[PDB]
Amino acid sequence: GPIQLWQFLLELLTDKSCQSFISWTGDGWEFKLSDPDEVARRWGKRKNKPKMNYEKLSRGLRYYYDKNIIHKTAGKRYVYRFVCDLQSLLGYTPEELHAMLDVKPD
Amino acid sequence: RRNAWGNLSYADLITKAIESSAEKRLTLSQIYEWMVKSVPYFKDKGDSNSSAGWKNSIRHNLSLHSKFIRVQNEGTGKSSWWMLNPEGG
DNA sequence: AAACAATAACAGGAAACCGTG
DNA sequence: TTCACGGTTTCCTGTTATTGT
Ligand SMILES: [Ca+2]
Image (cartoon, rainbow over all chains, first blue to last red):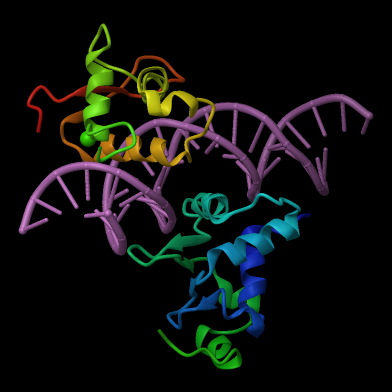
């Protein structure tokens, strides 16, 4: 059906030109929305919700905490973490994926 | 004239809103309505939403200040009563 | 130096919305 | 077809961090 937010973020996190606004932090499947308005804008375009913003996007991220899909990294602005089994879905370790995308660690 | 409405702080305003009530308690929504009906500056900011920057300042003052305490309200709906702290912290 | 204002990140309830089976 | 559901989207209440006055 319609793509789901978490799949959308993964899509952006696997495309290296998106790195300026959303990137892996280099710790596992922890990532950062370094420019959350640009990420929300794309999410709005993709779902055809022209009024999408980070306030609303983040609320959908917050429903994922109980579904153990994504969790918040407490005290780090705009930092979240996939806590589902990404290794199985992607066929790569964090280390492998980080090399592939030339991830400078945080 | 430190603020647009005068020398009163937000907190002094909320205090006056709550003291004006028959039962010495109001909901956030009622505090909003008081501001709009009672403080000349806010008189034309009535049909605006919680993102209003001054609604944010009210929520922010109600949680930050120990002089305000939140109390649960009976049925479903139907948000907390805000009252002054008998100790006034 | 301490109070207050401004503003935003964040948690999570409620209800509308809408595409799909 | 209509219907019910999940996944938001929208809005809100409440708590907290930060930076400017
Ligand atoms: Ca309080």
